[PDB]
Each structure stands twice: as C-alpha cells, then as structure tokens.
Image (cartoon, coloured by chain):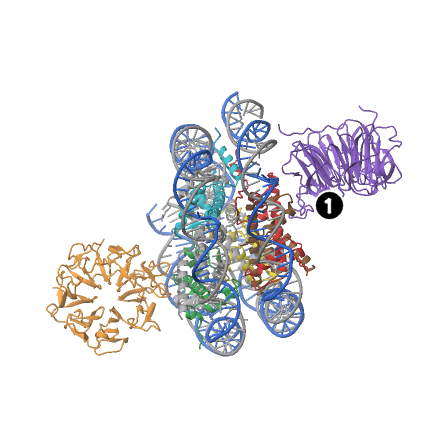
Chain colours: B cyan, C purple, D orange, F yellow, G red, H green, I brown, L blue
Amino acid sequence: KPHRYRPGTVALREIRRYQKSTELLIRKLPFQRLVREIAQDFKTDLRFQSSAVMALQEASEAYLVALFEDTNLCAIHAKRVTIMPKDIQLARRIRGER
Amino acid sequence: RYRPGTVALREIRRYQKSTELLIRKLPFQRLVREIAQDFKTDLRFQSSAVMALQEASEAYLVALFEDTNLCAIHAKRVTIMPKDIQLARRIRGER
Amino acid sequence: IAFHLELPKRRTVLGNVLVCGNGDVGQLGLGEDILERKRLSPVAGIPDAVDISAGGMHNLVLTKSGDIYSFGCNDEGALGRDTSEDGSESKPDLIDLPGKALCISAGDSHSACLLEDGRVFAWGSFRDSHGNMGLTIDGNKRTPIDLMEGTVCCSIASGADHLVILTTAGKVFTVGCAEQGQLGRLSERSISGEGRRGKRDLLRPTQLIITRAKPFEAIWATNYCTFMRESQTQVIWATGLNNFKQLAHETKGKEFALTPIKTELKDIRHIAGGQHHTVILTTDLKCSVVGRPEYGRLGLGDVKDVVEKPTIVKKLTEKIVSVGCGEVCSYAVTIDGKLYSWGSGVNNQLGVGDGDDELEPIVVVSKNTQGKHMLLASGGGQHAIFLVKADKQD
Amino acid sequence: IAFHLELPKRRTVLGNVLVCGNGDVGQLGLGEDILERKRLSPVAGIPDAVDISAGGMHNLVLTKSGDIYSFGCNDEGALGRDTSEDGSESKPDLIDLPGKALCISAGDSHSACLLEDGRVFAWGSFRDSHGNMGLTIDGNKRTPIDLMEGTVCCSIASGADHLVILTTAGKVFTVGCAEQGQLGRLSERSISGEGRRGKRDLLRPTQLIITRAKPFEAIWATNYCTFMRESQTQVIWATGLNNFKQLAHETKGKEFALTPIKTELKDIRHIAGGQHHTVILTTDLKCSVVGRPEYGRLGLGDVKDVVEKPTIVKKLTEKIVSVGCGEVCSYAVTIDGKLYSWGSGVNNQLGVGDGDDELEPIVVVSKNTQGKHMLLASGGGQHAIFLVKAD
Amino acid sequence: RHRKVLRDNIQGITKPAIRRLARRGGVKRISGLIYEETRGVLKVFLENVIRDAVTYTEHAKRKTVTAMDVVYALKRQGRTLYGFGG
Amino acid sequence: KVLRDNIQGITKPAIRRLARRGGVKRISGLIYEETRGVLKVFLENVIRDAVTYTEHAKRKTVTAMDVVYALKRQGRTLYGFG
Amino acid sequence: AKAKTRSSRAGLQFPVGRVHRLLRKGNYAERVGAGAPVYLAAVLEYLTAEILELAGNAARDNKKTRIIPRHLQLAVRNDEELNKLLGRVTIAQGGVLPNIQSVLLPK
Amino acid sequence: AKAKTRSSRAGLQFPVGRVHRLLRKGNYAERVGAGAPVYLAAVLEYLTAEILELAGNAARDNKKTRIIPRHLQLAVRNDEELNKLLGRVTIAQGGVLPNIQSVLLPK
Amino acid sequence: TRKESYAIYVYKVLKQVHPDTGISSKAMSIMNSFVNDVFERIAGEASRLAHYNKRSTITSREIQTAVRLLLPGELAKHAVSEGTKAVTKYTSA
Amino acid sequence: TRKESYAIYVYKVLKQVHPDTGISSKAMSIMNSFVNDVFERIAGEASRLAHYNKRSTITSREIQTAVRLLLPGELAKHAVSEGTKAVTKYTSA
DNA sequence: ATCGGATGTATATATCTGACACGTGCCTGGAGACTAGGGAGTAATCCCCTTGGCGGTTAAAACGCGGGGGACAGCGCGTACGTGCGTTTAAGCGGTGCTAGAGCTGTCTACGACCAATTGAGCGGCCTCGGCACCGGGATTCTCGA
DNA sequence: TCGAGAATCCCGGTGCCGAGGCCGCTCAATTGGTCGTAGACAGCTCTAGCACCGCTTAAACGCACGTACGCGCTGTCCCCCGCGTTTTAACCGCCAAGGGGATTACTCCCTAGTCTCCAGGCACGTGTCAGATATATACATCCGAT
C-alpha cells in the first residue's frame, strides 16, 4: 500500500521549517509589481530604489506573520484549529486596525 | 420579576448614556497611594492627580471590557470570562 | 397631554384656474403657441381645482379629489411627470402619486405635497450658488418620492430653493439651499456645502432646533426666509435672508439670519413674500408689508426708504382673506372676492396695466374677473396664477 | 559512527591512605587531637581505598566497592555528610549516595563524584571574590545533588572553585567561579557575575563551546585552569589563569584566557597543578613543569625565571606513573613505587625535610613509605594525601 | 509622626463597581472569575502609570505627585489624557 | 505602462507559508482573499506616507529612507535599511 | 507706525505671533520660516472649528447651550476621521458611544 | 599638550565627542551639560554590549563565528527586557522564535 | 504669574461657528489640551522633515507635509486648503 | 562624501565581549539603527524633561531620568550604574 | 398575536445656585523697523542605479483527486449567574485645623557657548583570505499501517 | 507494540566573495581662552494636602431562587490536507540607456537679533442666566395570561 502522512503532519513540519529559517516567503517580482501598482494611485511614474522595495517586503511579511500568530490564538480561542476570516477580523479589531 | 438579562441591558444603556465615574472615589484613592508606596515613601498627591488616574483607569478598563466582550461573542458565548480578558490583552501587546 | 397637531383640511371651494404673464417655458399652461397674457386667462384641462401653488417657472394645482396637475419648465423634474411627448409640459397633466394630497408647495426647481396620510412627497431639485444640488444627496427626482419616510407630517412650505416641513409633534424640518440661512440650522462655514460632509447635511431633511422653546404649530416660507410659530408663547420665529428686512425684525449688522430669531409679529393668518419684500396677513384681515420700495412692490406708493417695520397697506380698506407674491410683486384677495395687485409689471404679472409698475394696490377688473369671486393668488418669476370661484360647488 | 565515550573504570589497586601537614580543620583525618604531621601517617577507618582526591581543606576517598569517605573542613558542606557530632569531621566517614562512585574530585569548598550510571553528584559550594556563591543558584548543598540531571557523563575535574564535566557525547560543561576564565565560556563583563543575570550563568552547568572543534575526549583541571583534548587532532585546549604561564602557552597581552586556546602539549598522560605552577606527565612517563620558580615548586633547582615552556624535570631518573600538586608543592610517583616531592615545605606537606623548601625532587623514605609501593599523591591547602599499595 | 501603611485596598474595587464598568463596555453577562482577574489587570495598569508619574516627580525634586506628572506619564505610554493640563 | 491585478501575485502557497511561520496548522480557503485585502490596506498606508516623504524631497524615486521613516511614523520601526 | 497683528493679515483668529514664538522657543529647528506660523495657526484654527461645530450640534441635540466634555466626545467618536486623529486620546468625563452588540439583544 | 578623547577620560568605547555634538545639532535644548554626552554615550555602549553578548552566544550555539541578523533576533526575543525595549521594532532577516501552540501538537 | 492658553482664541472660533453657544471650563481645558497636542505633533513632524532633508529651517512646506502625514483623509485636504489661503492672503497684506 | 556611523564603536565593543566573533554587514546595519533609535528616544525624553521643568540645559540628570523612563527593569538599573560610573570617572581625569 | 398590569424612562415646569461670560486695569509680549550673516535657491555637473530587453534553467505555482478530521448543528444535563429584597458597611459630604512643601524671588556663582588654531580620529577606498554556503553521501530520527 | 519508509541532522571537502585590516586623507573634535546668564541657592509666602469628628444614606454585602446559559458529546458532510503531474513565470545572468540622485559652485534674500513702543491678552472682580434639581405626570416597554 502507498505511503501517505496523516493530515497535519506535513503542516507541522512546514511550521518547524519556516520558523527556523529567515528567508522571504513571498515572490520577489510579483510583490514588486504589487507595490508599484498600489503606488500609481499616489504619484505618476514613480521609481523605486531596490532596497526600498525590499524594506517594504520585510515589513509586510513581518506584519502578516505576526498577524497570523494573533489570528491563530483567536481560532484556538473558539475551540478550533482552523483559522478563518472572522479570526483575522477579530485580531485586527482588537489591535485597532478596524 | 424581569427576565435574566433584561435588567442587564438596562444597565448597559444607563451607563453608556452617562459619564460619571463608576468606581468609588475614596477606595480608589487608597489603592493609588498603596501602589505608590513601593516607589517613594510618604508621597503626597494633588487631588486632580488621583482624579486624572481614575479617569485614565476607568477609560482603560471600559475599553478592555469592550474587547473582552468581542472575544466572548467570538467563542459563541455571551458571558465574558478570564480567558477572554487574557486573549484581548495578548493581542493588544499587553502580554 | 402630549403636543399633537391635526392633519390640515383640503380646501373644498371649487374653482377655475387663471394665469397671466410670460409663458416661454409653458408656465401659462396654455399650449406652446401662447407666450404672453396681459389679462387673466382660463386654463382648461383641470377638473374641479381647489388650490393653487406658483413656482419659479412652473405651477401645481390641487383638485377636490386630491389629484395634482402640473405644468411649466420641467428641466429639473419640477413637474414630476413624463415630459417626453412634444409640447406636453405646456399643458396641465396628472401626477402619479401613492394617494391623494392635502397641501401643495413649489419653488424655483422643486415641488412638494402632503398626502392624505401625513406623508410628504417631493420632486425636482434644489439649487445653490454652485448650480444644481438635487432633491436628495443622490440628485434630481423626476418622479415623486417620500422625503420624510416614517414620519407623520401636517404642513409644508417652499422657498425659492428650500423646503420646510412640520410634523404632527410640532417638529420643524428644513432641506435645500442654505446660503441665505433659510434652513436655520447650519453654521456660516457649512451653508455653502463645502465642508468635509459636502452637502449631505443640506440635502437630508434635518430638524430645526431652537434650544428651550415650545413645539411649533405653523410654518411659512418666502423665497429665502422661513417663519415659525412657537406654541403657547405664540411668538413668530424667523430665519433667512434679511438684507432688506424681509424678516420684519433686525439682525444686528448682518445681511441674513443663520438661526431663528424672535420677531414682534403678532396675529398672523398667513405670510407671503418675494425676493426682497414680505406681505403679512393678520387675523383682523388687514395687510402689512416690509422690504425694499423699488418698483412699488410694497404697495405704499411713493416710498423711497426701505420699510423695516411691518407697515399696513393703506389703500386696502376691505377685509383680506388671502395674500400672494411673485418675485417682485404682490396680490390681495378680498373677503367679497375682489383682487388687488401691485409691484413690477414688466412681466405682465399684475393682470392690470400695460406693463407699468403699480405703486399702489390696483383692482383687477377684466373679462375673466369682472363680477367674479376671487379665491387665491400666487406669483412666480415671470408669471402669476389665480383661482376663481366656479359656479358649480358640487 | 556517532562520537561516544565509554564510562571510566574505577581504580582497582587496593591501598592505604596516608596524610601529612597541618590538620587544624581536620584535613588529616587523624582525629581532633592531631594537628600536624611531618612524616606520612596512616589514616584509620577507610576500607579498601583505591582512589584519593585532596581539596583545599578536606579530602575524598574512593573505596573498592565505590563508597566515598570524607574528612576536613565542613564549614561549606564539602564533606557532604552530617558533621554535627564533635570530631566527626576530623575522622573519615561514609557519604550517602544513590549508588556507587567511579570518580571523585575536590575543590577548596566543593566536592563531586561520578556514579556508575553516569550521573555527576556534587556538594559544598564555589567561591568568588565576593564570597560564597553556592553550588546552585539556590545556595549551598550540605548534601549531594545531581548536577547534570538527565545527561550522562564520563569524567569530572575540579579546580579551586570550578567544576569541569565531560559528557559521553564529547561535550564539556563548566560551573563555578569564572573570574580567572576557568569556565572558558564567558565575557569579561560577565565573569564577575554582576550582570542582569547575576550568578545564574556561573552556577548553571553550561557547555563550553569551541566553534568547529571536534568532540573532546578528556579533561583536566588545576586550581584556576581547565584543560581539554579534542578527538582526532589530539590538540590540548587550555583556559583560565595564566599570569605565570600555568597554561603552558602564551596569552598575547592578557593575564589569563577567558576562552580556550590551542596549546602545543603532546602525549598527555595526566595534568596536575597548584596555583602558579602546572605539572605535566606524558605517556612516555616523563614529568615536565611550568610556572613561577619561587620556593622551588618547579623542582628545577636554582631557577629564578618564570618557566614558560614545559621544561622536563631532569632530577627524576625513573619512569613516572603519577603526578600531584598542592597549592605550592608537587609530587611524583615512580613506576617502582618511589615517592618524590618538592616545593614549599613550610606546611610540612613534603613529608620530608624540616619545613625547608625543596628546590628539586627529594625521595620520601619514612616509617610508612620505605620499602612500600606508592600509588597516588595529591596535595591541598596546607596538607597532603597519598595512597600506598596494600598487601 | 504617624506612619500609615496601606494594605488590601485592591478589594475596594468592588464587584458591583466592576460590573458597572463592564456595563459601560457593553457586557451583558459576567463570570465570577472576572472580578478578581480585573483587579489584577487594574493593578498592573496603575503600577505602570504611577511608576512613571513618580519618576517625573523625583526628577522635579518634589514630594507631591502633580496632575501634570500623571498626564505626562500617560502620554509616554500612548494614553494621552485631555482635561487636566498639557 | 500600467499595472493591474498584481495582487494575484500573492498566491495560495505563499500566503500559507507566512501562516506556517505564524504557527498556523490549518487554513480556511476564505483566508487567502482576506489576507490579500489586509495586505493591500497595509501597503496602501505605508506607501502613501513613503511617497509623501518622496514628494517633499522633490524626488521621483522612492528611497529606502522614505519607507523607513514611514514605517516608524506608524509604530512599525524597521532595522537594517538605514 | 500703526501696528497690526499678523493674524489679521492672514484673516485668522488663532495667534500667528504666539505660534511663531512657540515654534522658535520649542526646539524644532535652528530657524523658523515666515509662513510657518501662519500655516500652522490656520490649521489649528480649522481643526478647532471642525470639532467645535460638531460639538455645538451635540449640545443642541441634547437641549443644552453650553458645550461639555460629553458633547466633545460625541462629536469626535462619531466622526470617522476625527476619531482616527484622536484614536489614542482619552477625553475626561466624555463617556462612550451607545453601542450594544446585536447578539446581546433579545428576540 | 597632546589631545585625549573625552571617551578615554570616561573609559568608554562610544564617542563622547560625537554624541555631545549630535545633542547640540539635534534640536533638543539650547544648552548641553558637560556630563550629558558622557552619560548618554555610556548608556549606549551598555545596551550595545548587552545585545552583542547575547548575539555572540546565539552564533556559537549554531556553530557560527559571524553574527548575522538572525542571531540579533534570537538574542532580543529571548530576553524579556530587550524584547520589551524593542517590542515595536522589526529586525530584517531576523525571522521568528519557534513556537507551536500545544493544542496543535498531535494527539 | 500669568499662564497663557488658547482659551480666548477657541472662544472666538466658537462664536463664529455657534454665536449662541457657550462652553464649560472643563470642556475649554480639553479644547486647550487638544490644540497643544496637535501643535506638538505637527511641529515635531515638521522638525523631523527639516532634519531628514538636512535643512535647518521649518517653513510652511514642512508644515504642509506634516499635516498630510498626521491628518486623516479629508481633514488633511481641508487643512492644507486653509493653510494655503492664510499664507497667500498674508503675503499680500 | 563622508557618512558617519557607529560601526567602528559597535565593533570595538564587540571585540571586548567576543574577541573571536565577527559581524555581517546587515547585522552591523541593524546595530547601527538600534543605537540611533535608542539615542533619539533618550534624547527626546530628556528634551521634554527640560521643557516640562522650564530648564534650557540637558544635563546628566535628564539623561538619567530619561533612561529610567525608557528602559525596562534591570536594564535601567545597570544603565544608570554605567552612566553614573562614566561621569564620575570623567570628572576625575 | 392581543391585551392589561406593573415598572421604567422620557418630558414639562417651576425654583435656585454657582459657574460662565463680560467687564476692567495693567504689564509684558509681539509688532516695527533696521542691519548682517549664511541657509537655501538655482544652475549645471558627474555617474549611479533604475529600468528593461533576450533567453536559459528549473523552482515553484497550478491543478486535480481521494478521503481523513475537523467545523458545525443539535441537544441534553446542572451549574452558575441574574434578579430582587433585606441588612450592613463605609462613602460622601461639611466642617475645622494644621503644616508640609509648592511656588516664588533676589541674589551671585559656575558652566556652557563660542571662537580660532591645531591634528588625530574616523571615513572611503583597496586588496586579501577564511567563514560559510554549497553538496554529496551516510548516520540518525520521527511517523505510521500491523 | 513491531519494522518500513521518509526527513532531518551531520560529517567532511571544495570554492566564492564579503568582512576585516591597512592606508592616505581630510575635517571634526580638541585645547585654552573669554564672556554672559542659566540655575544653584536661601529665604519667604501661603496654597492645598492631609486628617479627624460626625451625620445621612448611597451603595456594598449577603442570601435565596429560578432559568437560561456554558459545556460536553454525538452525528453529518464538506472541506482542507497530502501527493503526484503539468504548467507557469520567477529567477538569474548579460547587455545596455539614460533618468534622476547626489553633487558643486555662486549669490541672493530671508531670518535672527535688537531696542523701542504699546495694545493684545492676562488676572480678577462682578452679576445673571443655564442648568441642576425636584416633582408630578404622560409615555414607552416588559411580561404574564390567554
């Protein structure tokens, strides 16, 4: 019979992996385009220092990662192990973003 | 006899409508002086100082209960519990 | 008991509608081939009319059954009906309403009515200095809509570009242009609608509040003024343009009044007014005026100074049961049925004379008034509309 | 496969305990009426002694079965036993342990042992410039406690006020005073224990790490030094006090080493040392020394220069199978059973002479050594202890 | 010459009073364990604000904690307070 | 040149990775769109202030400092870019 | 010779001169531009008017003619933008906005 | 008379001279006391030393002799007091502390 | 010892927006605290702006940018509008 | 153009604490930003302390009080020890 | 769904108090007007790094198909919290009186700003090498159907 | 509980480039003066912080009671994980332009600093009207009964 891991096993393995490493988890180019796109609505024909785009991605991932930590506690608080949209919303509200 | 919860809602409305302080002034003042002992002995306070503290304190607690209340409702409950306060403060970065 | 007002009783005296003046935009309701009338002329198409209301460039008419007919400029939807067909705006036609109306009112670009159930329907739009505003914050309303939804009302009054509403609880509501303080409920820095909230506060019927003051029992409005009567005290509160003492009281070194002020007006049966003059009808059936003398709109004759205090018109010796005003002219209907008029005749609104300004009240005796019973009179910008007593009275 | 060290074997040669020197605080074990010996004297009460260890003011003795007897100054708990009754510290008595012991070690105010199962039990306390630190952060330990709970160890080594531990994985742990860099795992600002963490890092057995160095296979400790031998390369790493070249190597511009440094020591059979001198015994059974020459603690005769490079003791013609040190004295045991000593004799630790300093190795022949086969020699503060093979 | 030492004043923050606070916060039902948990939170809050307030007092070489001391303390902690000065 | 729909760049596998680092074990499918929206808002806020600094300096190029000063202004100080 | 406040030249109520002094003696820069105080006083005056208007309305809605902290609190917490600007400010004796969670209501 | 750095007089590695200037040109006050820069430089060196000492350990515990951002992170986040001093700060390439909630561990 | 505040200026503004409306002392204090706060925020930011750009002068430009950063949405747009008017009107008088 | 830094000083301290340890460019940048951050915080608070108390001079006193306010627990205590230590020693030479 | 009893809450009115608003005398902070220095505007330069094309390699995104396990509704039990009433506690208020210590003022000393001439610390630029990444392969560890 | 399978840890060798140490070279810190005022200090004024007596009564406490709520457990199913395969397009190395960041060189003009002058804004008195308070009452809402 074929070999399959149980649901959640690989998940935890991924958690341990990415919590140990420190590399950016978002794709460089796609993110750089998102930045430029969002920037269009503020000033026309903007140029970016390479480091400026990196500083944004660092701040963005650090922000999202931490947000997930809080989103996680909320799901767990409701006796669940699956994070849901309403979990993110509660976390942000408590923070003061909503 | 009013049904359980009916009078509670009435209290909610009453106090959300007013602005008076909800903690007894004198007992609070002693709490302040007691906590202050551990920093400087024989400290004196301006009345307005103690009052400024009570304003801040009650504003802080009221808001904390609002967040706490959201945590309770989140867990599909309507009764706030210590766990709810703990979750609120954790997300706030107070823990 | 709790303060409560009764829904007004629709007029019951049957009559025939008359008009005169310029009808370039079809405000004479006499087809599209008649642009001027120097004498009062009949208007066919309206069955059993009981009440009239003249706007800036249009007219509303109420029937004994409660139906409303309109005609005139519909460039803003002031008529509240499909003006699609050719030359259909220059002839009186029916309006589609959720019921029958008790009262009607009209301004320069808008119209309003009080249904038989207490609902206030309005259509068209308002207009400030920056052009069109729309009826609601959304814009124009070609077709009638409920303005005070879920609110029982008992009275309405229209200015040039503002609407006044009275609830059965004695609460007053104003909506529309505010640059003259006709709303009576906004700060000088918000009347132009250039605040952070734009024009949302102008275009939403909001309550007019005079801190510590009894409920109001009656409301009136001129072109740029709003008048109220506080219950018990019977005091008349006024707000709006006052650069010519239209409010009848003084505003300390100000050209207008942003919030209501006490006037020394007593015994008011009805209040009418144009741009720069106000005609006052007292309960003893006498007529008084205030405003600027130019073009004899005050009907006092060789007056050279701005009349500041309510001055009773001398030449009017009979009892008056009704008064009306155009932008710059005035009307008076006697208890017996005669009709007087005065002011600017440059637009042939006086029904008498050949375009000459009448400095003193002159009786209007022509084919369609000679030996007839006059009931109502109200003027607009370049025209005037009247209601003569019919010989039916079913 | 994976690096793994075997548990050490307990010594098997049966012998009799001998002592000499000052015994004020009962470090002679001869009772509370005997305060001084000038020749080696037999200690009564210990069955089948096989190994010995001399602290500053006390002593440890390992027996055939693995029991530990102790005697001396128990002011700090270094005897790991109840010393309430009078004169109970002036005579040897058993220590209560969960099991039997393989190795023993002693400092100035602390003791330690290695149980047959790989546990390291210790008692007493360490001492820095401020004073008592305690065995743990909690304070003194009048009675033995597992110090490396959970970890299996294969070796222990004690300095004056620090303990060195070796795990079966080749990892080295230190604990105690660190003001001489004997812990080899702390910055200058933290060796005093005056940081935000206080003495929490000094009193918690922490691994001594040398980045990108093989697992260590052996450890040694003098009064203020720690020595290690990393596998494969066989290099000897040293750390600690070095104001007199106790590390047998140079520390550029420093009076000591806070982190281990490479030494050119080769073929080390054993390392002993006092305070300002280190005695080195190689596998070819030749004895060498380093440190200051005062009071002839180097045994090189008339020398007035601080020996920086391991000089071999020429006066010793026989093969040496064991070396030992007191604070300021040294000992050598020949393969044929002889016993040589030298250094400060002002405390009658030399067991030969009349308190005079011996500038070179002098054989010790008294009523209790002549014709007998000596085995072990270890010195303490003002006393010395020996093991002589029995019949 | 009277040295008064205060003790157990945290109990002055009664259950009813805490209920009122929760009520203004929109809370409808309250667990009994809440009341003690709240006293602990309030204590930490006050300790943090008062500590800084007193730090300002000692700097000014004063024996009395002034309103401004509290105001400045609160501002430092991102809890600006209007209506007492500053 | 004009940019459009680049928010789709932030993919499912990329979002779930961030979550994994956040300690998340199980993720609702609805989370992904919710995250994209949250991220957009975040970037909008920071980039807006960044550009405001950029325009004040009379520059056409957003520098790293513009982003750093912006993040600091919002209580999200960043180390390692100046 | 005849003097005239800088506020009047800018058509302001707030003190341009005082603001200018506060800026110079406030440890903000070596030097302060001529237009800085005018611009700042104008902005302060605007924000003051924005809040005082909403507050005034609040007092009127509760049948009072004098503004009190409560009216200020109501004015601010009801204005999305003003709320944000004062999201970390606490108004003494201001109370809170009436807000009961929907689920808490009976049915 | 040869020159001695004010740093050396105070026995500091951080620049008392440079710090003193940054204060004067930093728009903080009209005057800067002679002891101020010495005291400040001293405090900066202390906090610098504190972080470095912890980062160093973190590097050794990973068989590295070169300190990288990841180590600075581990050092700060594992220290209660440093974590709080830098609770609103983000370290680039610092990563996150390993932390899995108990309820998520297999049962 | 005379202590100054924006009290009289706040009142002058109040009388323009609500001539028939007064204000309690506690409310006036809150208003005074608000002005001082906003002042410090704007001046502080303008201070940093001049610093970030290696300039030693706080001009109307730093003030404007500061406002754009500190004030939310429409508040900033109208604040900048008012600041512009004042400066314009001022330089012509 | 000369752009100053704390690098050399951070490195000197590094050699005193871990003589055999180095530091990457990015780590040195982070350390450099951290020093400036702490500098601004402390100096800023000291600035206000002088203002609050109507003083025009930033002395050791303000720096010390600023440290007590900004640094948590033991950090503050030891930071004050070091601060006082240095000033005392500096007064000697 | 309809209705009355019973309780709460909003509302009208009449009176009374004290805090707000306005008045005034005074002083000290801002407006005038003027000069001199140096920040900043402006022009023009050097060349960095931002941007954008080709084209190969392959990491990673996308897709789909089980099916295990967790979200969710239902529901049944009993504890615990709300409601209300009667007892009890001390808060609240006022009144009196003391004195600690906040606040102020005039001294006069000590310190910090300032400038000019000097020079060594600290910056930028340049190799050089060894720390570490990269890899491949074997030791060990953790998961999971019996 | 067992061994089979897949992942992670780890050990050693090879190669690459960034970190660390050197070397001119400024330019910022130092030294050593002088001058002026911030602030250290001492005395003095008097606010307000503190503390007890004692009356009133708001509010805390305590207890009994019933319900509606938290919580645990079972059943249903869809939805999210895991894995294999196909597909996209990120990633990277190379080449190359030129936008615009960073710089410099000059010179204007804007701002600090001053001394005189006087009116804006402060403290402080003084009177009245907004609102706190009380009460009688109409009105809105809850809840049990049917």
- Asked whether C42 or C276 is in front, the reply is C276
Q: Disc 1 sits on a residue from what chain? A: C
> Where does the C terminus of chain D fall, quadrant-wise?
bottom left
Percent coordinates x, y for residue G61 in the rendering: 61, 39
Residue F51 appearing in the image: no
Q: Is residue I19 above or below residue C338?
A: below
Seen in the picture, residue D219 relative to C295 is either above or below; the reply is below
Q: How many marks?
A: 1
Pick the front one: L33 or D359: L33
Please identify the quarter of the rendering in which residue L103 is found: bottom right
| Front position in the image: C231 or C86 | C231
Rendering quarter of residue D11: bottom left
Residue at 23% across / 68% down in the picture?
D327
Q: Secondary structure at mark 1?
A: loop
Is D10 placed left or right of G12 in the picture? Answer: left
Residue H97 image point, x, y percent: 43, 55
The quadrant of the picture occupied by the N terminus of chain D is bottom left
**Residue that carries the numbered disc 1 in the rendered image:** C255
Question: Mark 1: few, some, or many residues within 10 Å (few <14, many ≥20)?
Answer: some
Q: Could one spot residue C79 in this view of the protein?
A: yes
**Image coords of residue C312 (percent x, y):** 79, 35
Task: Identify the amino acid type marked 1.
Answer: Glu
In the foreground, L2 or H52: H52
C40 sits to left or right of H56? right
The picture places residue C238, in percent across and down from the top left corner, at 71, 38
In the picture as drawn, the residue positioned furthest to the left comes out as: D367
Left/right placement of residue C376 relative to residue L89 reads right
